[PDB]
Structure formats: C-alpha cells, structure tokens
RNA sequence: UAACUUUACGUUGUAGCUCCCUUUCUCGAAAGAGAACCGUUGCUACAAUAAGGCCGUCUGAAAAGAUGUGCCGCAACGCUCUGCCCCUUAAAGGCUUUAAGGGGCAUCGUUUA
C-alpha cells in the first residue's frame, strides 16, 4: 500500500536491505524500514572446500 | 562446484610368531634361566571402517535358508507431501478448539540409487 524502492546490498555472507518511500514522481521522501540478514557463507571456511566435499568423500 | 570406478594406507579389535619389560613363582653363594597375569615393540592375517538403516532374486504355507558387478546414511536447495513453530481471518465454546489461508524451519520433499 506504499510506494517505495527496495535497496539490496549483497555479499558472500550478508544481505542488507532498505525501503525508501518515494514521491508520486519517483523521488525519495521517507525512510521506512531497513534490516540486515547474515548467514554462513557456502564454503568450508578455512580452506575453500565445498560443504558437500566431505560428504561425497565419506 | 555438483557426480564416478578402483587401488593403497592409516585406526581399532582379535589370532599366530616376535622386541623389550613391571610385579609374583621356582632355581641358583651373585649373575641370571625358565615360567604366570598384564603391559606392550615389530611382521603377517582376519573383522570393522561413521554412529545407524534396508532391498532385490531363487526354494518354502510361512519360519527361515540360498543368493547379489545389491542400496542408503556428514550436502545444497525447496515447500508438492508430512512434522514443529508463528501469524491472519471465520465459526463455536483476553483462554480453548476448529476450519481456511499465509509463512519460518526441519526429524519433510528433490537431486537420490
């Protein structure tokens, strides 16, 4: 029900998101909601092996 | 990057031989020689190699036998199914239940046999 642009910042272990409500003419007027979502990055951390590798070996 | 077929080790447990050696026997004026339990060095063999769970075929009413280039098990992603949790709404007795609907996660699904 709100006219807003969603900005995403993506990295190997993080996604930051922001919502900015914009004008009728597409100009930003209000900062609505922002958050950060962090996860574990999809590799064996020290060596860069794949997470699946240990399972395939076994 | 996801997917293979095998080899060869290593680890542990058990068997034979073996290197040491702690105590306890027996001998012997010492030194030791042989022994018993255990420890454990080395060589060889077998079993297991995630912890756990299954199938196919043949003879049998079945029990079970026989049998095999037998199968899965540490991941990723997803919500079709199933489970837990969260929410919205409707109905009936802020409490409880039900239904529908929408999600998160998985002990659920797919890759996958």
Image: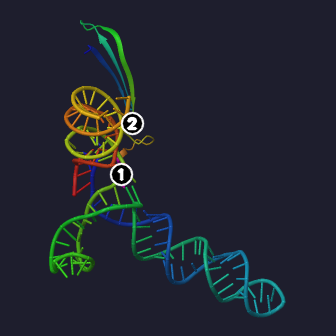
Lateral position of residue A53 relative to residue B23, left or right: left
> Circle 2 is placed at which residue position?
A41
Counting the numbered discs, the total is 2
- Of residues B71 and A1, the one drawn nearer to the viewer in this rendering: A1
**Within-10-Å neighbours for mark 2: few <14, some 14–19, many 20+:** few
**Residue A37 is drawn in which quadrant?**
top left
- Of residues B6 and B113, the one drawn nearer to the viewer in this rendering: B113
Look at the image and tell me in which quarter the N terminus of chain A lies: top left
Residue beneath the point at 36% across and 18% down: A33
Residue beneath the point at 38% across and 40% down: A43
Main SS class of the magenta portion in the image: helix
Residue B43 is situated, as x and y percent measured from the top left of the image, at: 49, 74
> Circle 1 is placed at which residue position?
A55
Lateral position of residue B22 relative to residue B47, left or right: right
Q: Mark 2 lies on which chain?
A: A
Residue beneath the point at 28% across and 14% down: A4
Q: What stretch is highlighted in magenta?
A: A52-58
User: Quick one: SS at disc 1?
Assistant: helix
Q: Where is B61 relative to B49, above or below?
A: below
Look at the image and tell me in which quarter the C terminus of chain A lies: bottom left
Q: Do labels 2 and 1 share a chain?
A: yes
**Within-10-Å neighbours for mark 1: few <14, some 14–19, many 20+:** few
Residue A35 tag number: none
Residue beneath the point at 36% across and 54% down: A57
Earlier sequence position, callout 2 versus callout 1: 2
- Label 2, label 1: how many angstroms apart (C-alpha)? 18 Å
User: Quick one: SS at disc 2?
Assistant: loop
Residue B84 is situated, as x and y percent measured from the top left of the image, at: 34, 42
């Amino acid at each position: 029900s709100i006219n807003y642009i969603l900005g995403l910042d993506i990295g190997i272990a993080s996604v930051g998101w922001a919502m900015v409500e914009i004008d009728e003419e597409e100009n930003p007027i209000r900062l609505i909601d922002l958050g950060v979502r962090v996860f574990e990055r999809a590799e064996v951390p020290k060596t860069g092996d794949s997470l699946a590798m240990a399972r395939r070996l076994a």
